Amino acid sequence: SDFDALGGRVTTVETRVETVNNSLTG
Amino acid sequence: SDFDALGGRVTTVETRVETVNNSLTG
């Protein structure tokens, strides 16, 4: 249905968590 | 269907990632 945008948001958050972790670890 | 709660959880995670990033950056 319309939860394709939900999947996109989930992917964005998945990448954002890793980005935050990597920047803070650096 | 019942994935409204899943959307709410996704929103909570979206806010939580930013909160963690901001606290740790501070």
Image (spheres, coloured by chain):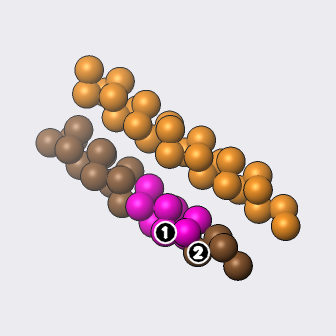
Chain colours: A brown, B orange
Q: Chain of mark 1?
A: A
CB-based contact (under 8 Å), mark 2 and mark 1 = yes
Horizontally, residue B18 falls left or right of residue B4, namely left
Q: Is residue B24 magenta?
A: no
Q: Which mark is residue B22?
A: none
The spot of residue A10 in percent (x, y) is: 51, 62
Horizontally, residue A17 falls left or right of residue A4, namely left
Identify residue for label 2: A4
Horizontally, residue B19 falls left or right of residue A22, namely right
Using the numbered discs, state the Cα–Cα distance from disc 2 to disc 1 in whole angstroms: 6 Å
Q: Where A16 sits versus A7, above or below?
A: above
Number of marks in the rendered image: 2
Q: Where A13 sits versus B25, above or below?
A: below
Disc 1 is placed on an element classified as helix
The residue sitting at the top extreme is B26
User: Which of the 4 image quarters holds residue B24?
Assistant: top left
Q: Is residue A11 magenta?
A: yes
Identify residue for label 1: A8
The residue sitting at the front extreme is A2
The residue sitting at the bottom extreme is A1
Q: Where B9 sits versus A14, above or below?
A: above
Which quadrant does the C terminus of chain A fall into? top left
Q: Residues within 10 Å of mark 1 (few under 14, many from 20)?
A: few
The spot of residue A25 in percent (x, y) is: 21, 41
Q: Which residues are magenta?
A: A5-14
